[PDB]
Image (cartoon, rainbow, N blue to C red; front, side, top):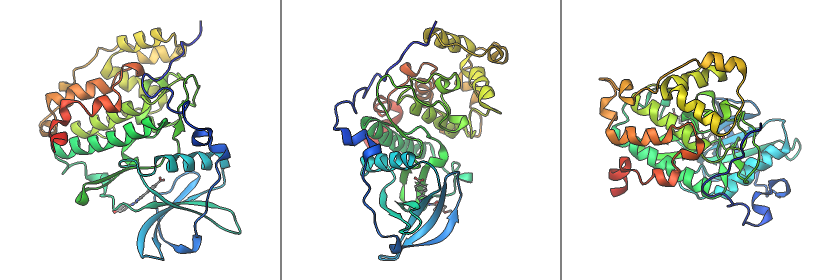
Amino acid sequence: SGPVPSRARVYTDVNTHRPREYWDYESHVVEWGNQDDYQLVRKLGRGKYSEVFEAINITNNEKVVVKILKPVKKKKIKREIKILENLRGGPNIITLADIVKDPVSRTPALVFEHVNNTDFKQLYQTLTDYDIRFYMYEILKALDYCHSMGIMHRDVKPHNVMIDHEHRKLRLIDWGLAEFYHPGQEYNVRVASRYFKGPELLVDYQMYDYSLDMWSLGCMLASMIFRKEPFFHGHDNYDQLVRIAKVLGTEDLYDYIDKYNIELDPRFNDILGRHSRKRWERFVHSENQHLVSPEALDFLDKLLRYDHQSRLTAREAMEHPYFYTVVKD
Ligand SMILES: COc1ccc(C(=O)Nc2ncc(-c3ccc(C(=O)O)cc3)s2)cc1
């Protein structure tokens, strides 16, 4: 008879108590840098709505990355910009070193610090058990910081986690989907990579929060220790939830939907079927045991939970024994 509302259990009113210019990006006035200080070197990846290039600051010969914002909606540009500024300086948060525009065209471009990212398409291998705990911990720092600042990343995935292994340097990037958290707001469930979409999104529950991001984190932790990227590999959004259900089980999935009085599509109930909750051990093998430990499994199990309200906060996660060595260090 109607979805049960929900609210973040932590940092719930973080933006409510701040000045109106902090989250009101629509009124944010941008200060422009000088476009002529940069020269594009080569195109990297791509994207819909943006063109990313490796570049060089002609003033200091320093490498930099430039994201040209293609014709879209100024609000979206204002949102990412305001967010990037609000987070500037945060631990492991990509640094927005400048903002420029074509004086004639008006086409906006975001200049970021450069990261000599180690090729991930085949790197998470040499990554030792300690390397994972370390980087996971570092990713946690960024999340707790951004969440602390009332902001949801919404696109946590391996591609948005730049890593310069040689320098043990990590950065969380592309805040293109990030949004400000305001208790009781209904958000767009169509964010984040499919393999990293949380149950809440998959069942169309819109009143979600920061917890979306630890689920995505949990997915990354899984793929990393079990050496299966992506861990949950669905064909489409519907199948994505089936992949999760085959691991976490259907009973818990149904208690969750029941709890929030969520209505699922009829056909969806047919494809979910019936599955038992499998034990994580079931996924460990000779090629990934060195990365798996009891602590890792306990931590992962506390991240990957249907009910977003029951997931660990980034802060609580940084306290898990899995990180004993890292912290100690
Ligand atoms: C193989 O060596 C490599 C060295 C460097 C790179 C590379 O892309 N470096 C990069 N450094 C920073 C990058 C970056 C890309 C997008 C965004 C955003 O917020 O949208 C922010 C920062 S990309 C890629 C490969």
